[PDB]
Length: 145
Ligand SMILES: CC(C)(COP(=O)(O)OP(=O)(O)OC[C@H]1O[C@@H](n2cnc3c(N)ncnc32)[C@H](O)[C@@H]1OP(=O)(O)O)[C@@H](O)C(=O)NCCC(=O)NCCSO
Image (cartoon, rainbow, N blue to C red; front, side, top):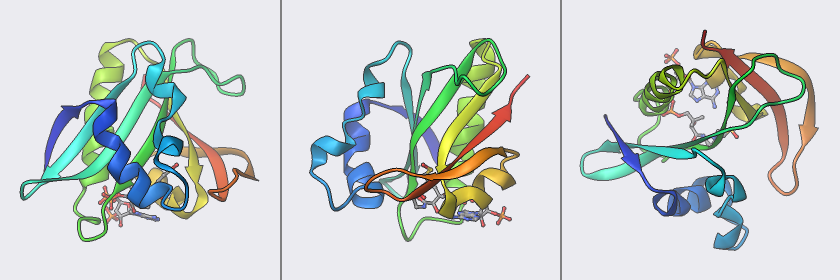
């Protein structure tokens, strides 16, 4: 797996295929992509972009840490899961975030992926909530100080 920078526009296809296939493509054009300091990483395997992850600065009112980043659009293509593609993106992002002085990385995780974030050392906070039309989510975070 090779981790490389990618542009926001490079994430839309996999966001649409994996996360939001039953909505128009504009639903994958996350407004947070246009927030200050946003960046995106791709995981490449055998000539193909097969994993994506997007990050931007956002402080959650219920999490503690002066500088925080949110993860959006975490996805790995079927066929290429279980190869540490996603973990590789998160670890590479943690380097970038640590270098920027970020204290914490958080995600409104799909509950179906909660065990993935747990393996990466994230904790859950609060309760499960629903996010139309993409189902149950739970706040998860990782302190990176
Ligand atoms: C969740 C994920 C991005 C994981 O990507 P991946 O590239 O397969 O992850 P990975 O780095 O290989 O997996 C790391 C560890 O977590 C585990 N894992 C992966 N997906 C998991 C899940 N959904 N639930 C529990 N554990 C999971 C792996 O088995 C691995 O554990 P081991 O080291 O013990 O073998 C991918 O399954 C996916 O795209 N799922 C569908 C979309 C999704 O739910 N994305 C998360 C969005 S949060 O808003």
